[PDB]
Image (cartoon, rainbow, N blue to C red):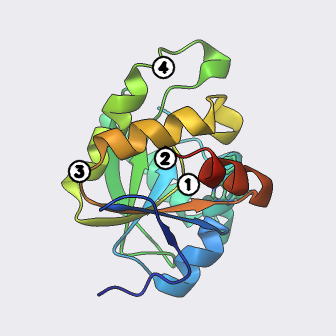
Amino acid sequence: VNSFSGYLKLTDNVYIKNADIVEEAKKVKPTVVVNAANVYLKHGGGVAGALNKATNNAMQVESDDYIATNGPLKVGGSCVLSGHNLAKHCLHVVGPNVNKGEDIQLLKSAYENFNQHEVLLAPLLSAGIFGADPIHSLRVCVDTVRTNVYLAVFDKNLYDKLVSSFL
Ligand SMILES: O[C@H]1CC[C@@H](Nc2ncnc3[nH]c4cc(F)ccc4c23)C1
């Protein structure tokens, strides 16, 4: 039993809710919240900008030190950093950005990072400003992640479409 509430169950291990991931993180304080990161960990907008804003820019300060030491992430890769006031840990995962021409096949590699964590609160990778089809992203999630994932979908309209079209 865990503290996630109000989710619809899609599969054995995948759950979904219409929620603001920032507010969901603030209430649950999950072990892991996933950020929709880019390779530079520049948290300017989308999920990343909202998560970073909720940390009062502490996420960005920590991220800049990470990049200065380690260099950029790979598309499809991840790193574990602090969850600040939102979670124990933040798993920064880089899905491909269609608006930059990155290969959508890398979306499966991105979701594989979730399998290193038993339970996660996450957004749909490559959705929103990353330009992928969220229905495709949900399918890849279900077919790739084997650990327990709680998906927060900010837009109520998209949430309804994702549920109604789910196979
Ligand atoms: O909107 C759709 C497309 C992308 C996906 N993004 C999110 N998913 C879950 N929680 C989210 N909180 C946010 C706060 C923001 F300022 C911006 C985006 C998000 C956001 C859902």
Residue drawn 68% across the image and 56% down it: 159
Residue 60 circle label = 1
- How far apart are labels 2 and 1 at the CA level? 6 Å
Residue drawn 63% across the image and 32% down it: 130
Q: Report which residue position mark 2 lands on.
A: 64
In the displayed structure image, the side of residue 106 where residue 54 appears, left or right: right
- How far apart are labels 3 and 4 at the CA level? 19 Å
The amino acid at mark 1 is: Gln
Q: Nearer the viewer, mark 1 or mark 3?
A: 3
The amino acid at mark 2 is: Asp
Q: Earlier in the sequence, mark 3 or mark 4?
A: 4
Residue 72 placement (x, y as % from top left): 40, 30
Q: CB under 8 Å between callouts 1 and 4?
A: no
Residue drawn 24% across the image and 60% down it: 117
Picture quarter containing residue 62? bottom left
The amino acid at mark 4 is: Ile
Query: Where does ligand 1 appear, by image quarter?
Result: bottom right
Residue 40 placement (x, y as % from top left): 50, 34
- How far apart are labels 2 and 4 at the CA level? 27 Å
Q: CB under 8 Å between callouts 1 and 3?
A: no
Mark 1 near ligand 1 (CB under 8 Å)? no
Q: Report which residue position mark 4 lands on.
A: 104
- Give the vertical position of 72 relative to 50 (above or below): above
Circle 1 residues within 10 Å: few <14, some 14–19, many ≥20: many
Circle 3 residues within 10 Å: few <14, some 14–19, many ≥20: some
Q: Report which residue position mark 3 lands on.
A: 115
Q: Earlier in the sequence, mark 3 or mark 2?
A: 2
Q: Secondary structure at mark 4?
A: loop
Residue drawn 61% across the image and 62% down it: 51
Q: CB under 8 Å between callouts 2 and 1?
A: yes
Q: Looking at the figure, which quarter contains the N terminus?
A: bottom left
Q: Nearer the viewer, mark 3 or mark 2?
A: 3
